[PDB]
Every structure is written in structure tokens, then in C-alpha cells.
Image 1 (cartoon, helix red, strand yellow):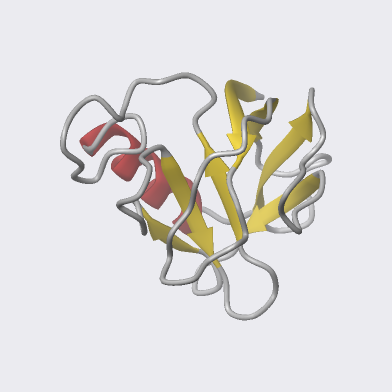
Image 2: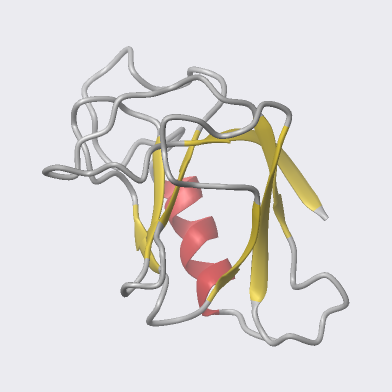
Length: 127
């Protein structure tokens, strides 16, 4: 429904560190495929398949209190949209373009207030 360019970022965490492996795809904000599961998919999907990491193509639901919204969990490399889960496979996503990583970090993954506000609202929302 609402599409943007993104990749995956690593599942690999050591101290919540990550290094980008350049991988392309698209993220799509949806309210479900046929809108009856109950929860709001972020469908990721490849133009280049995920590598270096345990992650695969996915259609993944944002469930309150099982999806935390983390603005950036790292400080090695910017551009970290993190959705972290309670031992059900956490998924990290990465901004495909550079709009972050020229400046000191904050809540940046692209932007601070916009993304933070978008992420919290889609997250709570539930069908």
C-alpha cells in the first residue's frame, strides 16, 4: 500500500553492533494482505536476496508488546530501523539510500521525529 526503498540489516548482534551488507528490496506498510489477520504487515521483499545474515524474504506483523520500536540500537553504522521481538526472530531493516551517516547520531535512521511518530502509530494499530 505505502512503499519505500529499503534493505535488510543484520540479525548479527554482539553488543547490538551492525555493519551494512548492501542488499536491495522494498518495504511496504500494509494493514494485512486481505486485511483479516489482525495486525499490520511490513512486507519486505528482495531485489537482491539477503546474505551474510540469517534473515529471509518475509511478510512480518507488528504486534504490540512483541514488536518494540527501537530508533537505532547501534552506533557503528546509522540507518537502523529496528523492530526487535521476544525470541520469535527479530528483524532489522536498513535504509537503502544515505540520508544519515554524515552527522552525529540521535534517533536517526533517516529522520528523528517523523519516523518515530510513524512507527509508533502503525505499531499500536491493529485490525
